[PDB]
Image: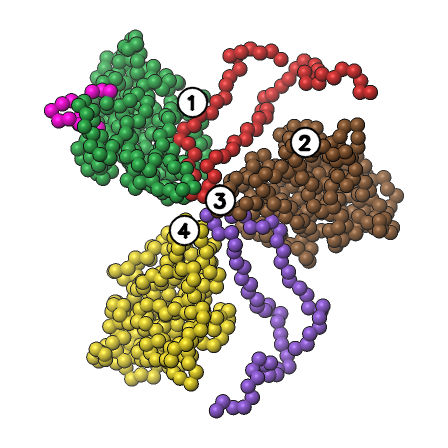
Chain colours: A purple, B brown, C yellow, D red, E green
């Protein structure tokens, strides 16, 4: 939950050539990204998720 | 068949299985004992300089004529290899230039990718001399021209004489590859170190020139993207130096 | 490499050699002795129900959002398997959903084909409940929507929340396949029977939901046919029942 | 350097079918020719090239 | 996989590895002892006549109907084989007709390439007879027609009756091949010598007819070249003669 700025790393992507298409192919395209963990992954010190803000019981 | 190449703990390039051209028949290697004249040991920086330096992509348009880079000035700002050109006096390195294009099956064209050792170039004005600012930029290409150049201290950049006063179809004498967009996609040339001395100062001397000339021009219909990006990737091989000092300049 | 699959003496499907997804890691199988609670024997109709039920084709247009079928209601009228849903009380079946598209090489797009066990869905109006007529049709797909649905007893059919109140990119947790028209063409998922009881009545309970969501939308130029047909083919596996009686209804 | 006419051979090329392209491909194209020698090649009686006409020394 | 075929010291044809049709099941061969009736020896010209005679290319347009060549008149002017038809009296030869098209992947169509032994043809006017000038040209094709021909001494060149009064779909009875532009590109049929006599005079008799009929017509969009060239290449096999004399005519 802490923000060490300039202590995480950046993953950027740059155009090298462009995107060359024949007559009949659409010129613009789409990339999708997929993130996961690896085999060396571990966690510690369980707590409550920051996402759920509701506190009182439902009804 | 889509095998990845990792060179150093920074670089990843994806490439299929294709043909290579190895120099004049030799692989780059390290200097042995009965080959040098210097009074010291080389101390090669193998642990840090062997990686892929992917330069900026050029746009092969319909009306383009050709591009050249002079080496080793083409990696003057590229990372630690540019630092070794500063903080040393002599240097010796082979290269593995990998050139590839991203075209569709509805594009057509043909490139010739030459590595010209000692490509000394004539000036656009006779009874005059070139400057260093017109031979090469530090990282970007220098364009050939269809018509005649006419400057005072520039290079004769007409395309069919290749800047050297020869026939452009005879540049096939030097290590070369043909990128024919119908069948081929990529080109990879492994240049050794060619000089008359075992080690030279890599600021004044240009070891070779990488020329990329389109012989059959690029054609496409109206749906198509009106360029083909040509991406060059240079990886130094067996680089070794001598003469540790400060940077000049700077 | 174009191997044909014949399942029963009615069905032929032609398919190349590609990748399959097998469930949560198990193949569908028949019930053993230490797994059931019912007071009788299953009497599985293996001789008549194992065939390919190719549903109607949907048209993947440029502006489509996604489709879902609820199972086993998706084979309610499909032949003898629909008759066994009538003239029985309990049922237990795995499925082999095979999804494939017919696109050209000048089309582009990407689909995600999920099988969601117990995909309970929320209503479009809070403080209200869904009806059975808005959860699923008997054989045709139910469309997701780009905007917000606003009915009284309908389903919240917005596409990025997948009807369940979650992130649509996290549906990759369940058995899934990506149809990427650049490289992939087909998708085949082998779902086992997942429940908390060994056999359930297959009128009230929806065992799983097959969702097909386009993540990268379909693009094409002006020559092209302005849709890609997605054909789903469901083949039941190891179906076994209990409780022979009349049909209700009807 | 001699010209024996009709004593060398001709290499011609003729259209057989045409050039069939789908919608989107460019209709006109390009051929390149590459000539070399073979393993049985030999020369004799060295002399001066006809191409260089300059005679006086440079400067 | 792009294997070259050289037949004699004049011919080169480039072709991939595909399917052949061998006659009625026999390869062409030389005449043995208990097969002939003539009073002399054959003296086969194997050293000079076995090469590839690539005829002129026809243009498969959108509205074309079909083409036929009569053999052995189709090689009447083609080189030394035409000279042997002059300076002999009897002859006997098999052939290896190789038919191939140059289409793109954006073209579509289907051809049927038949070799019809004794394809005797009816006239366009009943109670009349054909002339030899309407049966075949010496090297160019003869076109079928969509509508009804109406001449006096011509051939009934309507396409669905194939000039013989039969169904055009039943020509599959004779040695044949389908050029389907989606999957196939070429067609190669190896015809033996079929006659009721061991040797016939190859001026009056037409041994067979090579018909090329498009069953699915050629379609293309507006970018495309509006024809597909069909190139036929005939190579004679095991040719042997008798009756050395002068040429008549001439």
- Dot 4: what SS? loop
Q: Which residue is mark 1?
A: E8
Badge number at residue C224: 4
Q: CA distance from mark 4 to mark 3?
A: 15 Å
In this view, the mark in front (1 or 2): 2
- In which quarter of the view is residue C208 placed? bottom left
Badge number at residue B222: 3
Image-based side of C46 in relation to A38, left or right:
left
In this view, the mark in front (4 or 2): 2
The chain ID associated with circle 2 is B
- Dot 3: what SS? loop
Q: Looking at the image, is B99 positioned above or below residue B47?
A: above
Q: Residues within 10 Å of mark 2 (few under 14, many from 20)?
A: few
Question: In the image, what residue occupies the spot 84% across and 45% down?
Answer: B89
Q: Quadrant of the C terminus of chain E?
A: top left
The stretch of residues the image draws in magenta is: E119-133
Q: Residues within 10 Å of mark 3 (few under 14, many from 20)?
A: few
Residue E43, image x and y in percent? 32, 15
Q: Which residue is mark 2?
A: B148
Q: Residues within 10 Å of mark 4 (few under 14, many from 20)?
A: some
Residue E5, image x and y in percent? 43, 29
First-in-chain label (2 vs 3): 2
């Amino acid at each position: 939950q802490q923000d060490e700025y300039t202590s995480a790393g950046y993953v950027t992507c740059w155009y090298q050539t462009g995107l060359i298409v024949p007559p009949g192919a659409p010129p613009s395209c789409t990339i999708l990204c997929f993130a996961s963990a690896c085999n060396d992954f571990s966690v510690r010190n369980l707590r409550d998720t920051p996402f759920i803000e509701q506190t009182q019981l439902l009804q | 068949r889509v095998r990845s190449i990792t060179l150093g703990n920074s670089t990843i390039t994806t490439q299929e299985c294709a043909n290579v051209v190895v120099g004049y028949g030799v692989w780059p290697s390290y200097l042995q004992d009965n080959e040098a004249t210097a009074e010291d040991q080389p101390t090669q920086p193998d642990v840090a300089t062997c990686r892929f330096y992917t330069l900026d992509s050029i746009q092969w348009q319909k009306e383009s004529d050709g591009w050249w880079w002079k080496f080793p000035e083409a990696l003057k700002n590229m990372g630690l290899f540019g630092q070794n050109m500063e903080y040393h006096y002599l240097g010796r390195s082979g290269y593995t230039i990998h050139v590839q294009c991203n075209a569709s099956k509805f594009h057509q064209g043909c490139l010739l990718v030459v590595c010209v050792p000692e490509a000394e170039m004539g000036c656009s004005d006779v009874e005059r001399e070139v400057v260093a600012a017109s031979l090469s930029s530090e990282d970007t290409a220098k364009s050939f021209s269809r018509t005649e150049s006419n400057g005072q201290h520039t290079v004769q950049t007409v395309v069919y004489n290749a800047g050297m006063g020869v026939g452009v179809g005879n540049l096939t004498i030097f290590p070369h590859q043909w990128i024919n967009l119908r069948t081929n996609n990529s080109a990879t040339i492994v240049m050794p170190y060619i000089n008359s001395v075992p080690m030279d100062n890599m600021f004044r001397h240009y070891n070779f020139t990488l020329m990329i000339i389109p012989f059959a021009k690029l054609e496409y219909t109206e749906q198509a993207s009106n360029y083909v990006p040509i991406t060059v990737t240079v990886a130094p091989m067996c680089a070794e130096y001598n003469g540790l000092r400060l940077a000049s300049h700077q």
